[PDB]
Image (cartoon, helix red, strand yellow):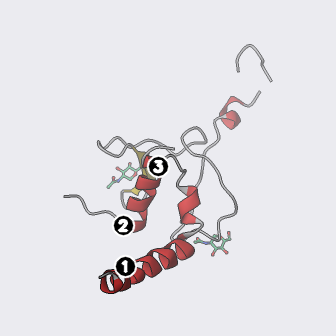
């Protein structure tokens, strides 16, 4: 296991889906907020689903 | 373009991800996008241009 | 670049 800063890891994965990494470094803040909000709604979804 | 910016303490290099092979940072293996104040953790260094050494 | 000789 080789340690790597987490934003650079996500930049690699962005390359993996055909989007250039500059797109990630310029929207880091917004992306982080979107990810946090989604994770927050996951638990609510699990709890509300019968 | 491919790899990661790796510095060995005093100098900066570009190297392919899965095997250490440092190269000089030049205009050929990098691409530009916008001004340099929005990206976090950016550093400073000389980016050589191969057209200058020819000096026609 | 050589043939152009700019
Ligand atoms: C510890 C290490 O890698 N040091 C290198 C040195 O050997 C090399 O000569 C220099 C560039 O000239 O860049 C730095
Ligand atoms: C991260 C970094 O080195 N930023 C510097 C900045 O502080 C300085 O004002 C500018 C002037 O050349 O050069 C660059």
Q: Chain of mark 2?
A: A
Between residue A27 and residue A42, name the one nearer to us: A42
Q: Is residue A14 above or below residue A40?
A: above
Rendered image quadrant of residue A29: bottom right
The percent coordinates of residue A12 (x first, y second) are: 42, 53
- What is the residue that sits farthest to the right in this orientation? C6
Which of the pair A40/A50 is nearer the observer? A50
* First along the sequence among labels 2 and 3: 2
Chain holding disc 1: A
For the point 39% across and 78% down, which residue is it?
Answer: A39
Q: Residue B52 location in percent, x, y? A: 70, 37
Which circle, 1 or 2, is nearer the viewer? 1
- Tell me which chain the residue with mark 3 is part of: A
The label nearer to you, 2 versus 3, is 3
Image height check: is B47 above or below B44? above
On whether disc 1 and disc 2 are found on a single subunit, the reply is yes
Q: Give percent across and percent down for residue B22.
A: 38, 43
CB atoms of marks 2 and 3 within 8 Å = no
Q: Nearer the viewer, residue B36 or A15?
A: A15
Q: Earlier in the sequence, mark 3 or mark 1?
A: 3
Q: Residue furthest left?
A: A1
- Answer yes or no: are tags 3 and 1 on the same subunit: yes
Q: Mark 3: which secondary structure?
A: helix
Q: Which residue is mark 3?
A: A15
- Residue C1: quadrant of the picture: top right
For label 1, the residue is A42
Q: Which residue is mark 2?
A: A5
Which quadrant is home to the C terminus of chain B? top right
- Decide if ligand 2 comes within 8 Å of the CB at mark 3: no
Which quadrant of the view contains residue A25?
bottom right
Q: CA distance from mark 1 to mark 2?
A: 26 Å
- The residues tagged by marks 3 and 1 sit, at their Cα atoms, a distance apart of 26 Å
């Amino acid at each position: 296991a080789l340690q790597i800063p987490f934003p650079m890891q996500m930049a690699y994965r962005f390359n993996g889906i055909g989007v250039t990494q500059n797109v990630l470094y310029e929207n880091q803040k917004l992306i982080a907020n979107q990810f946090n909000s989604a994770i927050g709604k996951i638990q609510d979804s699990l709890s509300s689903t019968p | 373009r491919e790899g990661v910016f790796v510095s060995n303490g005093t100098h900066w290099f570009v190297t392919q991800r899965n095997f250490y092979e440092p190269q000089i940072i030049t205009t050929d293996n990098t691409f530009v996008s916008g001004n340099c104040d929005v990206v976090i953790g950016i550093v400073n260094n000389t980016v050589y241009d191969p057209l200058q050494p020819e000096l026609d």
